[PDB]
Image (tube, helix red, strand yellow):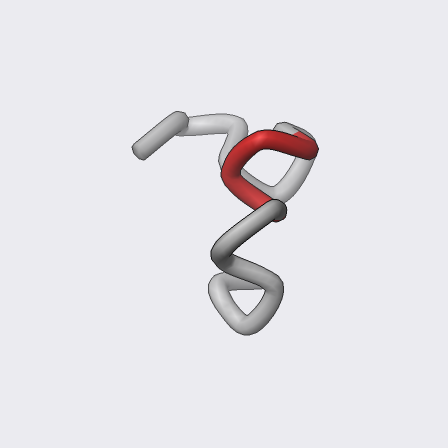
Length: 19
């Protein structure tokens, strides 16, 4: 997971409730 996960569209991708 990225430390910029909420900025990161790629983390965002599967993780929209992460932030």
